[PDB]
Length: 313
Ligand SMILES: CN(C)C(=O)c1cnn(C)c1C(=O)Nc1ccn2cc(-c3ccccc3)nc2c1
Ligand SMILES: [Cl-]
Ligand SMILES: [Mg+2]
Ligand SMILES: [Zn+2]
Image (cartoon, rainbow, N blue to C red; front, side, top):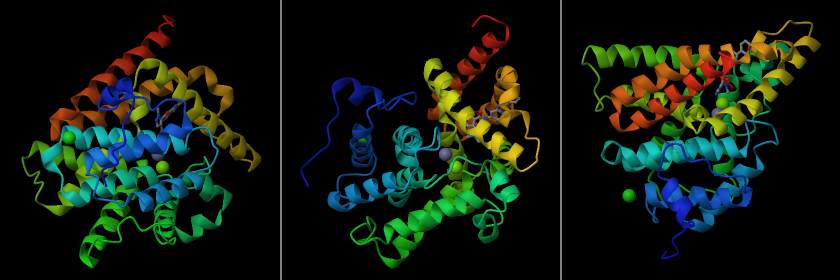
């Protein structure tokens, strides 16, 4: 009970900031996650023996891929930790528990390929889950790991509290399907602009949690430029292997996944920032003002990509 996780001073202080990078030491990441749960939720919410065993099983089921890996899981969790901790009063007890766990599990057993490619390949998962294919898989993995003996970190919840948390986790994970982001943000934009936004309406909270999940998932765009730039190399390493795989099916891939169009990445980034990233963080700061520091870092990174196009780096 009285065994609190502590971080070295620099991490203890910087972990609280939105732009914290979790570092290149793999074996410190589970520690960093528990630290965040204990501070965000409390030292009671999970039994440590069960929580440590769940983290290590989750870790085992992320694959050694360039981007969609264990580091991404912990990184996405840290961004949510920072939102929760800057918006203390807005979230329930179940929400703080479920969301750190959703984020850690939100890409479980990712193979480094898009839903689109799974469909063009005719992968069996595309047959089982016709929309949001990889995301329904991520949740299915999350449930299977909770059901391993001694892994049920939610064991002490009541049947209704347990069903509520699993439902928060499912919705949270499905929302990381970027194909669903566009409509969600639009509705939230509309509801914020007409004053209809009501955090006591559950369908409204669901949408706000969705937008949070997108924001945590895209959060490489909110880091220090050198983090943002080097993460982009890993992101493209996956895109370009997917394009290779597309060309093996006799399909010309989109420029994003064509390593031949490597020259045009900078412009492709400006489009992603304007089309996806900046709208996401703008709407999130409208709804939750203390997340403004994500919008500001994202705008700085847009300007860094513009300095790349102009030949200033
Ligand atoms: C994980 N994921 C799915 C992401 O989208 C994601 C998450 N974080 N970040 C930073 C991204 C990301 O890079 N998005 C995009 C989206 C469209 N593009 C188009 C091009 C492009 C076009 C022409 C030429 C060369 C490249 N490049 C991109 C990149
Ligand atoms: Cl606190
Ligand atoms: Mg995903
Ligand atoms: Zn992700």
